[PDB]
Structure formats: structure tokens, C-alpha cells
Image 1 (cartoon, rainbow, N blue to C red):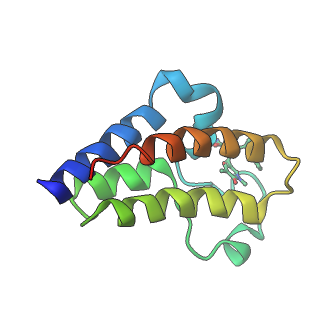
Image 2: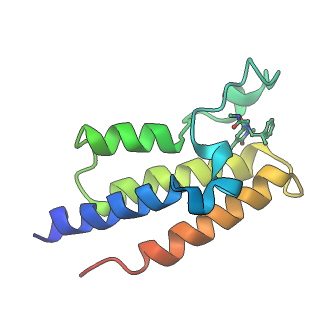
Length: 112
Ligand SMILES: CNC(=O)CN(C[C@@H](C)c1ccccc1)C(=O)c1cc(C)c(=O)n(C)c1
């Protein structure tokens, strides 16, 4: 019940974050940052634990997450990495803030 039900809620949130509804600001978070491709040669010196929605999806599909807290920690790690690496006035930070608003408001509706 509880753990399964809470992970169903997490899976629902994940599907929404990946949905066309949010694509305009979610797209930078779909796949791992390709630091080399973008010439971001300091990315892996600054970000020690990269995270993205494809990694969260793989972990959910593999039943890696044992509870909602573990799932939420990865989603927030993804946003934190964005806030750590990028100047706060960058468009990717505006997109991060918007997708995190979607995440936090629906995560708060967790079944007890
Ligand atoms: C499929 N391609 C992409 O997703 C390209 N981007 C986003 C783009 C707006 C961007 C490029 C270069 C520097 C900053 C932002 C990224 O790979 C990306 C995504 C995040 C969260 C991030 O924090 N960075 C630094 C980079």
C-alpha cells in the first residue's frame, strides 16, 4: 500500500514532467548534460553527481527507488546542479525554477 502508492504518485509526477504539457521548459532536463558537446569543460569539476529525468526514469523502471523521499532527492539534485553550475539569470535557471514549481506543488499532494 503506502510505499507502492507513494511511488505510484512519484511515477505520475515523473510522467507529467516528461509530458508535452511542460516540454517548453522541461527539455533541458530530459537527458544528461553532455558537457563535452556544449564545451562545458568545468561541468564535471563543479557537479560531482549529475542527474536528469532519463536517469530518474531508468531508476523508477528498475525499481531502484525504495520510497518517495529517494525519488524526490534525485529530482531536487537535478535542479540543485542547475542552480549550482549556471548564473542565476541564465534561461536554463528560469526553466529549472518553472519545472521545480510543477514538481514541488504536485509532490506536496503525496498520499499519506
Ligand atoms: C538537449 N540539449 C540540452 O539539453 C542543452 N542544455 C540546455 C541549454 C539551454 C544549455 C546549454 C549550455 C549551457 C547551459 C544551458 C543542456 O545540456 C544543459 C542542461 C542543464 C540542466 C544545465 O544545467 N546545463 C548547464 C546544460
